Image (cartoon, rainbow, N blue to C red; front, side, top):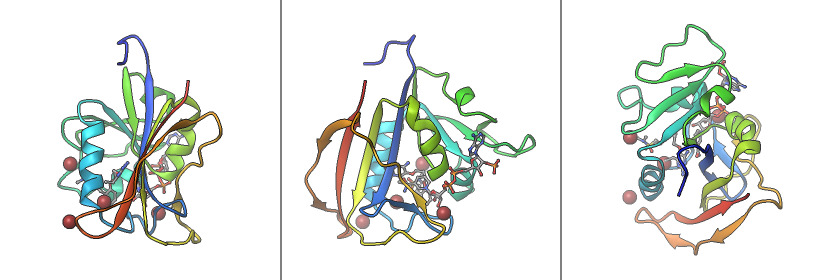
Length: 166
Ligand SMILES: NC(=O)c1ccc[n+]([C@@H]2O[C@H](COP(=O)([O-])OP(=O)(O)OC[C@H]3O[C@@H](n4cnc5c(N)ncnc54)[C@H](OP(=O)(O)O)[C@@H]3O)[C@@H](O)[C@H]2O)c1
Ligand SMILES: CCc1nc(N)nc(N)c1OCCCOc1ccccc1CCS(=O)(=O)N(C)C
Ligand SMILES: [Br-]
Ligand SMILES: [Br-]
Ligand SMILES: [Br-]
Ligand SMILES: [Br-]
């Protein structure tokens, strides 16, 4: 439960075991169960994304429905119809509940304010490569539960972590 006067900042991402979350401006796998999970967590809340993550969303679909979409960019004239564009992270974090939904740069910026991380680990052995977007590594202040590996319908194995801190 979030009191309406507070500011709960959460991060939600899917990563390969290695930490890779993005490559060539795309997520380098597809996992429908994780798409559904991402919706269940974020629906009804503000979502904050960096400009490159906005670009990675299909044009017809963005802004993602049922959520207040916020795009972080330093480009004053950036066009993101249906979203709002802000030039600093702190300006993006005024709602009672906010989910930061990527990418690599914006997770790293937001982590100091965050008290929840909802992580999907994908059992794909993509090694970290030059130019990849990477997930944060959570330090010892973060704690929580680790789910069991399961086969998705597609065959790709995954497990869910729900972590938090004070
Ligand atoms: N697997 C997952 O869960 C997941 C989720 C989301 C995204 N992704 C992937 O991650 C990749 C994108 O990540 P990324 O790290 O390259 O980019 P990003 O974090 O999505 O976006 C970076 C952009 O955000 C803006 N920005 C960054 N810091 C800022 C600040 N302090 N103030 C204002 N604006 C700021 C800048 O926009 P301007 O250049 O316009 O100024 C910057 O170029 C893609 O491959 C995407 O598909 C993966
Ligand atoms: C489902 C991926 C995902 N999962 C987790 N757990 N956290 C994230 N932040 C997260 O990213 C959501 C925002 C980026 O979405 C992208 C980006 C590039 C390529 C594909 C997708 C999937 C979009 S979607 O299928 O879910 N949809 C139509 C909006
Ligand atoms: Br990338
Ligand atoms: Br996906
Ligand atoms: Br959607
Ligand atoms: Br499937």
